[PDB]
Length: 127
Length: 129
Length: 128
Image (cartoon, rainbow over all chains, first blue to last red; front, side):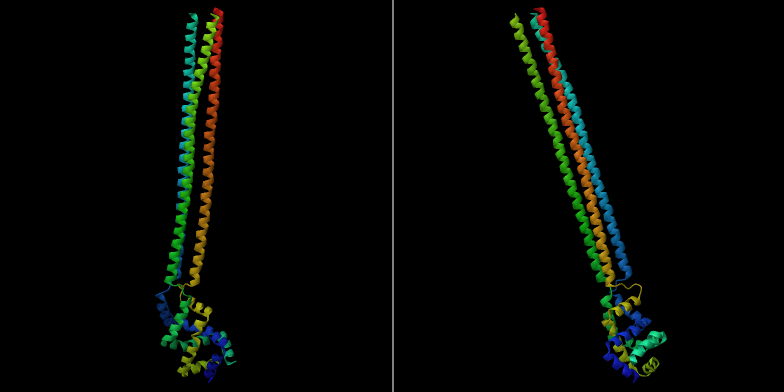
């Protein structure tokens, strides 16, 4: 009769049903045999906090690996570029030197050419 | 009112809450459809192996996309740099050539300048005599 | 009231059954209750929200790296452009120095020839 009344009120009042379930239901689930049965059933599909943490850890490592590789790839290009620029600087120096030597060569050749003509004219005059 | 009172007592008395729940537990264990309702409800919230696999797959792809983009961005700079260096190499070659031509020009100009003066002097000598 | 209820439940199995059938379905209707129950079952239990939070964090971590990488590449582009400009200035410097030196040589040889011409003209005149 007490329970018959309670059943009746629960059919009528959804807020009562909700409130009462929130009191009793957690306790029913605390039952260890029931808890084990529920866990066994869910375990076929469950992803655990440990599984998520393992993915988090792997992701963090994969990102760190890429950051590190990227830093190395950029550094390799910096080195290669510095090297190419140094090689071009050595070519410029080589040209400067060759240009200098060639100008000294030309200076000497023209000096002697002029001197040869002078002797030629002096000899012609002396006639 | 009867249930309102009951709710109040349950908040206050944990032994009552426990005892009343234990009166229900046997039926939940006996009735596969209550068990199914509970499992259906819990599955609505539970993370699954499928969910984690989908995130794993998406993450792997997102990282691969960045690796690939990064490789392309570095490659684009390598090509642009190689091109600028090649242009500077062509300038050096152009200067070498222009320097050579200009020296040959100077050689010829000075040869003819000297020769012009020689003819000038020879003519002057001859005229005196 | 609850003491009476407990007594009736011990006596009446149909009441225990009926009451359980009323209260259990609340788990399907009540998201907060359903979540509480699931999290109480075990420390290992994870929710769909837990996966979404990792997804959100991962997306941000990748975006942070993309943005840093873009900046690091841009810094190298600028530094490289600068080094290339410095080389270009060296090439220009050599061109200029080469030009000036050739003009210097031209003038030196012209005056050398002119000096010799005056020398010869003087020598001719001294003779005649």
